[PDB]
Image: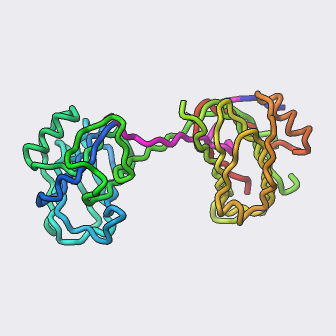
């Protein structure tokens, strides 16, 4: 009695794809002997971007003058959020026409509108003409939030040589995109059994696929037993993150399973034993019903995702 269909917003399982948007970059300690730090962001395709700023781990407070060169193909409204950045310090922002910068405030700070080149090397050259040395360069495929850790890190060489394989935890951007699925809702004894069949987690091997478990409500914690049948064509590590749900948790899969500390505390997780599950909705619902997991609540088939939001009834 499972009529498989493209799922709607009410389906209990909602798939998402999380990704880091870095394309290329560099970092340098070469600004140490210069009066200011220069950080370049080169964004690729009104748009709003939150720019989170904090010092590198080896610094308690950051007080060195800052220069941000914020390049984008279309205008952007920048929202600057800072933590442990000393007030009253001269911080400059170079943006494109139509772009603006807003802060969580006039005190040694200005926004300059520029004509900026689009090529990475040309933008780096534009910066070298105004400042002798640059602290970081990050080319990004887009983003909702950009996280920059300011300060001259000693691990870096003296120059900024852009590299398409460069990655620093100091300069990161995150993007989360909802993904479509097919599936069906079928239905008891304060238990829910959910079958998630993922075709691909993104060819990055043994990557994490998060299963986030919460009440649909969000304000009221639930007493519910949960059974998860997790199947993937590729090798994945299923990461279980339960919130505001207490009960038995049974996981059926041939893959490895990581449990969050909150999950092990909230729920009574049965020792996961590797289960060889069949493929397809028909064979998976039948397997569940034959191994004492009755009734099945839902089945979800997802072509691509590395994050699932499972919301339990009431």
Q: Nearer the viewer, residue 273 or 279?
A: 273
Q: Is residue 45 left or right of residue 250?
A: left
**Placement of the N terminus among the 4 image quadrants:** top right
Count of marks placed on residues: 0
Residue drawn at x 12%, y 57% is 34
In the displayed structure image, the side of residue 73 where residue 313 appears, left or right: right
Residue at image point 30% right, 36% down: 163
Give the quarter of the image for residue 64: bottom left
Q: Is residue 268 left or right of residue 123?
A: right
Q: Is residue 20 above or below residue 191?
A: above
Q: Residue furthest left?
A: 129
The residue lying toward the viewer, choosing from 7 and 275, is 275
**Picture coordinates of residue 97 (x, y %)?**
17, 42
For the point 43% across and 46% down, the residue is 174
Q: Please report the bounds of the magenta region as a residue range.
A: 5-23
Which sits in the foreground, 24 or 9?
A: 24
Give yes or no for residue 258 being in the magenta stretch: no
Based on the picture, tell me whether residue 6 belongs to the magenta stretch: yes
| In this view, 196 is above or below 153 | above
Quadrant of the rendered structure where residue 147 is?
bottom left
**Quadrant location of residue 128?**
top left
- x and y percentages locating residue 116 in the rendered image: 15, 38
Q: Does the rendering let one see residue 222?
A: no
Q: Nearer the viewer, residue 12 or 66?
A: 66
Q: Main secondary structure of the magenta part?
A: strand
Residue 314 coordinates in the image, percent (x, y): 73, 57
């Amino acid at each position: 009695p499972c009529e498989l269909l493209p799922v709607g917003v009410g389906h209990p399982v909602q798939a998402m794809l999380k990704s880091f948007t870095a394309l290329s970059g560099c970092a340098s300690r070469g600004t140490t002997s210069h009066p200011q730090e220069v950080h370049i962001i080169n964004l690729r395709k009104t748009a709003e971007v939150a720019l989170h700023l904090r010092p590198i781990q080896s610094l308690h407070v950051h007080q060195k003058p800052l220069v941000f060169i914020l390049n984008s193909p279309q205008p952007i409204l920048w929202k600057v959020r800072t933590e442990k950045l000393a007030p009253g310090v001269k911080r400059i922002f170079h943006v494109v026409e139509g772009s603006e910068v807003h802060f969580e405030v006039s005190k040694s700070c200005e926004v300059k509108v520029e004509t900026l080149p689009h090529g990475n090397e040309h933008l780096l050259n534009w910066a070298h003409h105004r400042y002798t040395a640059v602290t970081s360069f990050s080319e990004l495929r887009m983003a909702h939030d950009i996280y920059i850790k300011v300060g001259e890190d000693p691990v870096f060489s003296e120059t900024c040589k852009i590299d398409n394989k460069f990655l620093s935890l100091n300069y990161l951007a995150s993007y989360i995109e909802p993904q479509p699925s097919t599936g069906c809702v079928l239905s008891d004894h304060e238990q829910e059994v959910h079958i998630i069949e993922l075709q691909a987690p993104n060819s990055a091997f043994q990557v994490d696929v998060i299963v986030d478990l919460r009440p649909l409500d969000g304000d009221i914690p639930l007493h519910r037993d949960v059974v998860l049948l997790l199947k993937c064509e590729k090798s994945v590590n299923w990461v279980i993150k339960a919130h505001k749900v207490m009960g038995k948790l049974e996981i059926m899969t041939s893959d490895t399973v990581s449990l969050s500390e909150d999950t092990e505390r909230l729920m009574q997780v049965s020792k996961t034993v590797k289960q060889k599950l069949p493929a397809g909705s028909q064979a998976l619902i039948q397997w569940a019903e034959e191994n004492g997991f009755n009734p099945v609540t839902s089945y979800t088939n997802t072509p691509v995702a590395n994050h699932f939001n499972l919301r339990l009834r009431e």
